[PDB]
Image (cartoon, rainbow, N blue to C red; front, side, top):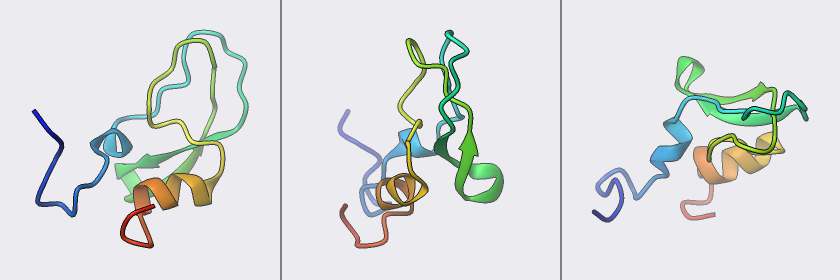
Length: 71
């Protein structure tokens, strides 16, 4: 229902573990890893996968890190 309000409406999917997919294509993607509360470079399968699968760190940051409030 709705989104994780309160937390300045932040994308919970960002805190979602990294998910490359099935096809071990690997494309050096990025994801917000809670392990380091930041965007970490993780491999990316393709086909399947998940949400937390950015292509650029700044992209994973703008969405996750959400520097400029929104994004």
